[PDB]
Amino acid sequence: AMRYVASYLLAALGGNSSPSAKDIKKILDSVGIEADDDRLNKVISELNGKNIEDVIAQGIGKLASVPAGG
Amino acid sequence: AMRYVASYLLAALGGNSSPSAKDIKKILDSVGIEADDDRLNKVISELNGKNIEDVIAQGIGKLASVPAGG
Image 1 (tube, helix red, strand yellow):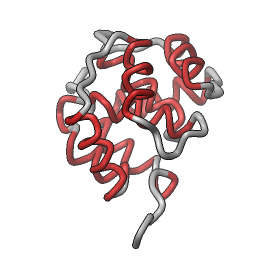
Image 2 (tube, each protein chain N blue to C red):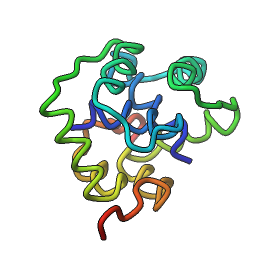
Image 3 (cartoon, rainbow over the protein chains, first blue to last red):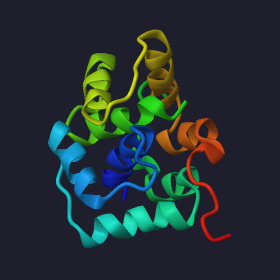
């Protein structure tokens, strides 16, 4: 569930600490990523109820980086 | 060091698994975030040498979410 976290984070850093899922969609539009509303708000809500790092390190996994040179 | 991770992630999810720091800048431009080159590539390199979740959960911290209702 790392798809929206990227844009969620960006929006937060851009001054919008409480980012709307629509904004998320737009930021995903910038790099060409899909975005649902329900799942998106759920991921957002995860990050909101937990710590970003926590939700990240749980909901990303080895989808993040493959061992390049390892 | 979560500033670039957001856009780094987005770029990765947008099909560019090995994202250029310039792309990062552009994605940060979308939401209005600053971006150096050295520090940026360093954060990127952190995420590249480690796991994203790991680097995130290390280099974000309580900068992520404040206890809203806690």
